[PDB]
Image (cartoon, rainbow, N blue to C red; front, side, top):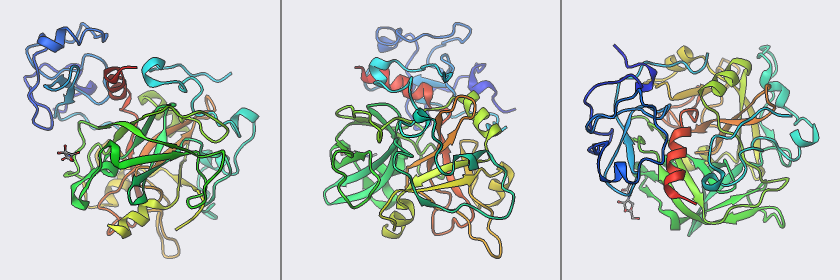
Length: 388
Ligand SMILES: *[C@@H]1O[C@H](CO)[C@@H](O)[C@H](O)[C@H]1NC(C)=O
């Protein structure tokens, strides 16, 4: 019954997006005059105004919608549930002229991989939890997470969220950091700033940290806070590209194949932050950047740990709580990075964005993270729309 291949074989008549936007006809005005620069697969049939997946979009079928030239949304199909959790060789997916620079060299930290030095806990990521001792969260080493980004409210100045650097110019965070009506949150570009290269939360880091304005915010078109933070994803463009350093460097983004390889080889991923998730919940506390390694949870155990429906776009991490052992629920910075290291190409990849399940009033077992592995075609279409 379920729709396979992310809807690439689909031949039905669904012609509205998840958010009620009527699809435009594939042959239409700005669907033929400003929508042919993109390379489509001819085996897919672009019929009338029906949702289709002609570009191998891991997210699924989509269609053009009214708005600016190239505007589009995704459609609601019942995709088959997919268990993603099943020199330096890397090749660049995005156009550097719209992505900015940084992709070719992503996930190789100047102070670690580039000097053939291992950070203090990375070997832990590839080791089965022997039961026994756990390596607890501690202060990060200098340069350990040079893709770490802080999102601030401009006025009053206040740390709002974490985020992550994916190029010199683009940053990923959770949509609920920008738009969350339950907490009366509706931030536009001019309400915010970001600081990059930071280690200390409270000390100005002369010659190291960088501040930046945001030029543009793209909330994911599937974002729906109503149904358990569905597609809790946002992409933000820096008004001025940030200069790379020993302290500022982008993380890599994985496709489905790379995600599979990361979860097949690793036992654990890594969460870095200033405990902002725990703090903002209490609003709606470490002064130095923290790092903790957390085991990936088996999907059935994740499904059984919570009341809500856990979709295949979401995963749990943390140690299982016991009579003498608390878990790692609500770890990290809201919208912050959950990363994994590839033992195959030595590079770091973001695997999730810190989210929540029922939230910190009833999440007590594991933390919840939104998968990033489906995002590449979305990011591609967004950056090509924005232009250079
Ligand atoms: C937030 O307010 C903006 C004004 O900047 C307005 O355009 C918009 O309706 C609000 N955003 C949402 C998602 O409601």
